[PDB]
Length: 104
Length: 518
Image 1 (cartoon, rainbow over the protein chains, first blue to last red):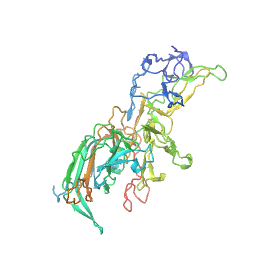
Image 2: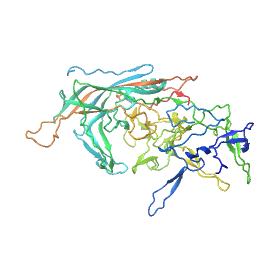
Image 3: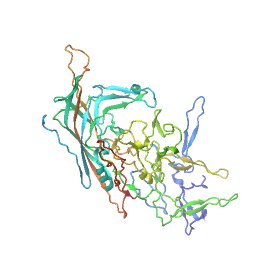
Image 4: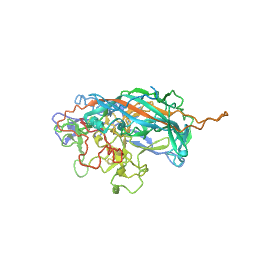
């Protein structure tokens, strides 16, 4: 319902034909939208959720904090970033001891 | 096959085929009588009731076990060099264990002089647990392995295990195992024991470093076709805001986009070797990263795999994250820093974050015209979908394999201390002197016989492991780092015997010298 904003560094930004190198106006580029993927995936600009930070008691109220980042859990499901016609087809998975879901 | 014949010969050699090396090694051992032929339960309360966080309940057995889980057992320092200089990766394939030339000796102690005599008919009994039914203690990096130097004689360690407890008290689920209830193989002098084992397929260990870091994978000559937000404020003064974009390229290196990110981090406290720079407080236990289980804090010893000293400053090390090996002839407690050997993670800093430093930074709120942007620090990070790392390095003094606990699920079960995690590892090999009782009373008595004969056994073991090698294909032009000996003169030779006969290993030796492209 609000498309006015976008994640700072999380979005893909493509330039329009004949676009300068530096300090080009917002209308010179093409900003990518993640809208489709919001069913399985959290909003990039918002916290993942909320979690209890202490134990309640008769004396103590319950305090809960914000989860800013979250790793994988065992029940967790997501999708990969969308494939644009202006974007990369493949990538090389670095050769390493271990990697998780090596999708670029 | 008799008393006079020999059970087997001494076969110790390393034969290097192109793709595989076979390391045979033979030692001679001495097996005492533990617990006076008794099972006994042990707890903290047996040692002392001082700690809750330190609490245990378990059983010590008369049995003892062979442990060959360190590389120095199977490799000479020259064969380790030949391995780590010429090969990218190595993996174990098969294992062959022989036990032969067993000889049992009764100690008859007369109060004038203690006398030792050979006992021909006595037996020693040996079984391997191939069903992994007994608790598997080998993967814990306990002392008691084969000695590194083939000429030493080693005493076999006593077997024991821990089970569930609440405090020092047992739980209904705590299980008691009778090692005597098993089909062991009894054998006398003139009998030999052997078995073979084939390692389940595991990934090669990486003996290579990386020749380019994860954050520089790009072409330094060419721009990306993607843009970043370069400027927001359009100038000093009120109401100056402009979204301005720029092509990420060689000029601004950091802001480029990347397909992959470094591995997870669990932050460690940073301790400096030079002692004046450290805080004047007991921060060891209080200020250390730990993990709690069942209301019980287990200090986080090498949990993740992370670079140690960042770069250019090696003076410090992660508090509990580093591996610390002791030098030859080192005390048990409060030994000085120069008595031990501190391991360096330096190689792995290309794909992995520095252990002592935060993983990164993250936005903690939404900006607005009224509100500034606040960002916090990420102290620990889990796996993400684009995340890449490497495993901790394999030292010649360190563990070869570990047993992956049998559980519903696990992620990348590589042992955090090092080596090859295995669902079914090489089976434990347990050995005990069969008891010979002293003269029983002439009248029958219900009570079990508590009087035995002082006795011990000897013999030789042969541990033959077959390895699989991944050879260096590297195409780089310039020469490569290798492991060398310091040419400069010294009173002694490194990795050689002393004047009084004490063998020692001067420093730890990792596997990562050769490099490879990331």
